Length: 293
Ligand SMILES: O=C1Nc2ccc(C(=O)N[C@H](CO)c3ccccc3)cc2/C1=C(\c1ccccc1)c1ncc[nH]1
Image (cartoon, rainbow, N blue to C red; front, side, top):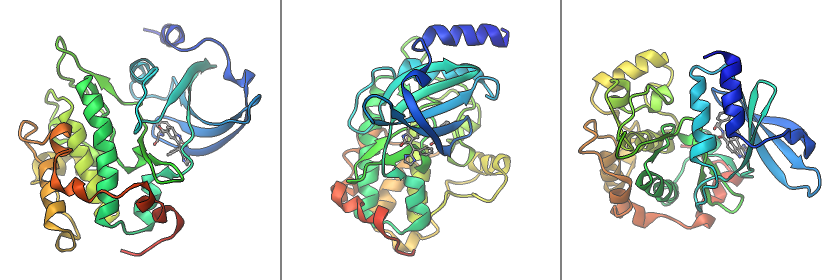
C-alpha cells in the first residue's frame, strides 16, 4: 500500500480534527525510537498532558502505529498511563496522554541505588498491570525502565504501549521481531511464535537494571547483544552477592529461557519477594535525592 493509503486508513482509526485547536505550549520533553514526547497545556483548563508524536514515514513498520490507538482506547487501570485521544496532524500521529510528573524509572536507576522494598514495589505495580493485560491477550512487548512512569507521590504506571500486540484464541501467538534489543526475550529474538511470556523476561532484565544500573550487554552493539541473549545462559546480576535470596529466587523465575517454564504474571504476584513491596511513600525519596550504588 502507498503512504497515502496508509495515512487514510490510520485517519479512519483516530479521533477527527486537529488538537492544535485546544493545546498550547508544546515543548519537547523526551523521546523514544519511534518519535518524541512534548508537554502541552489544554488552553481552556490549564490541564497538562503529554503528546507523543510519531512520523508515519519514519517507522520501521508503520502498521504498528495502529496497535496502541486501537488496543488501548478507553483502557483504565490504576497502574497504566491513560490515553486521552489520538489525531493525525500532517504526516504525524499524535497521541495525547496523561502527564506523569515523576518521570521515568530510567532516571532513577541511573542516579541512585534502590533498596529491595522499592524494587519489590515497582515489580508489584508492573505485575498488577501485566496480569490484567495478559488476561485480555494484550502483550506489551517493550517492558524496560523507560516504560515505567511515576507520580510525585510515588505511584507506578506502565506506559510506552506503541509496540503492544493482541493475541486471541484464533491467533494465540505473535511472530514479529518487536521490542528493544537488550530487553528482548530469547524466543522472540529466535523468531519463534511467542506470547505474553516475553513481557516476563523483559521484566527480569528491568530487575537487573534496578539492581545494577544497566541491562546486560549494554555497551555491546544491539545485534550482538541479541545474539548473546539468544545463545548464552541467562544473564547474571553484577551485584549478585548483594541481593537477598528472595530477590534472586524471584529473578530466577523471570529469566527462564524456556517460555513454558517461565513464571506468569499471575504466578509472580504470589511470590514472597513481593511481600517486601513498600507503599508509594517508600518510592518518593528516589526522586528527591541520590544514593550511590
Ligand atoms: O509524563 C509522561 N507521560 C507519558 C506518556 C507516554 C510516554 C511514552 O510512551 N514514552 C515512550 C518512551 O518511553 C515513547 C515516546 C515517544 C515515541 C514512542 C515511545 C511518555 C510519557 C511521559 C514522560 C516521558 C516522555 C519521554 C520519555 C519518557 C518519559 C515524562 N517524562 C518526564 C515526565 N513525564
